[PDB]
Amino acid sequence: AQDWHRADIVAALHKRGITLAGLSRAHGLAARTLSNAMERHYPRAERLIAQALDMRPEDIWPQRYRNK
Amino acid sequence: AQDWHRADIVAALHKRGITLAGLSRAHGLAARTLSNAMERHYPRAERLIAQALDMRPEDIWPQRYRNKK
């Protein structure tokens, strides 16, 4: 029902040994691109994070995808 | 840097227990007046939403206000 917090997303990545620095460098992104997606909706960055967690972005961000 | 999305603005209002239906009725607005401001710039309606969130509209819509000159 409620969106994941930045702290939920980061922790879950750390569970699988991923970092935002590492996941940004890998996909060729600017630093804040993934960090900003923790607070403010950006579909293409959310698809990258969802797939890193074997998920659909709609399950991490149910509200973001309902409020559009 | 980038403007807030409709989903960012809505969510933030819901955080404080506000809805667009409620905020429209309060300020005497037509339904779509606030909804349209989520997509397309309208200064006086965005000033209303900013103040509901203890903010300046320039922080919610940095691009709209930079893309005005």
Image: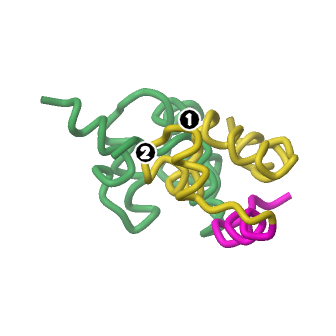
Chain colours: A yellow, B green
In the rendered structure, which amino acid carries the disc numbered 1? Ser
Taken as a whole, is the magenta stretch helix, strand or loop?
Answer: helix
Residue B60 position within the rendered picture, expressed as x and y whole percent measured from the top left: 39, 50
Q: Is residue A65 left or right of residue B54?
A: right
- Quadrant in the picture for the C terminus of chain A: top right
Q: Which of the labelled discs sits on residue B35, or is there none?
A: 1
Residue B16: image x %, image y %? 60, 69
Q: In the drawing, does residue A56 fall left or right of residue B58?
A: right
Give the percent coordinates (x, y) of residue B55: 36, 63
Q: Nearer the viewer, residue B48 or A35?
A: A35
Q: Is residue A39 above or below residue A29?
A: below
Which span of residues is magenta-colored? A1-15
Q: Does A8 appear in magenta? A: yes
Residue reaching furthest to the left: B69
Chain of the residue under label 2: A
Q: Is residue B45 above or below residue B42?
A: below
